[PDB]
Length: 160
Length: 160
Image 1: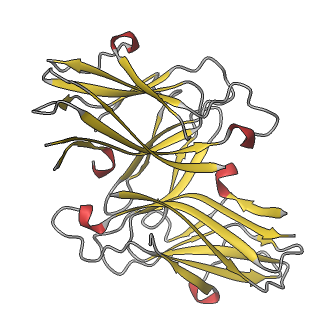
Image 2: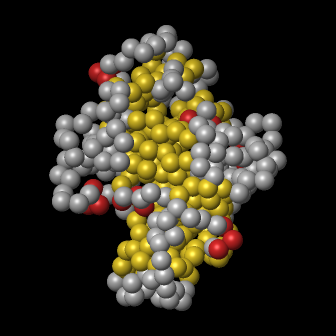
């Protein structure tokens, strides 16, 4: 039985560091129900280190969590003239905590789970897992290093 | 050889009728390069008839055009309490013209190509074609009938 801890597409207050110039919330709030997506596309600028951090998530009885990501990646060749700093990967991180950090964030406190690879707008579904988890809760975070990516769905579950 | 006539994700002025309450432009314009997507999610309201129309596209020497769509669909069961009017399909239309209609649009002047089916946020790639085309140009259009859908990529090409 999959027990869902987090389902982004189904409804957040996610932290972006930097705010504005890094990951950006895309939204349609003009219809019956909202569509939200975080994206980033600083493929020209170099030295990108853009962070997106989920809300705090309760661990409950989970020991191994599964993280399912759906996302687009635009290929670096599709940017005219060359995008020499463009990447087609991004990184998946997490941190455990017995307490809500609120808006406090430091990338150095997070532990890498994996580089996420796609293997001209390419659709992707990737799943990773991590455990054992032991604390009251945890955060996930996404580090962008200069890719052009829209996050469509983030689902975290464990198996009971 | 595929000759590309339209590539939405790679950069529009697309018409929405209705404007605001129908298809909505989602955008990230805060980074080096833009990410744009049209979406719609009026799954609660009933009697939806929302239109999104491309720019005018030159036919050139194309006779049969291929239309490649990438998109998400959120399942109707994922809306709590029941979404009795929710759909998981949308329709693909086109119209030929020797002249630019500008912002003029009438749905009755367009011809259906197909219902697009996906077969909780599901990723999709669908391709359809249509021809023979014979006029100076054409428009594509997307009719939403009450689904929750984000259009990620629209590519139109012909084979030379």
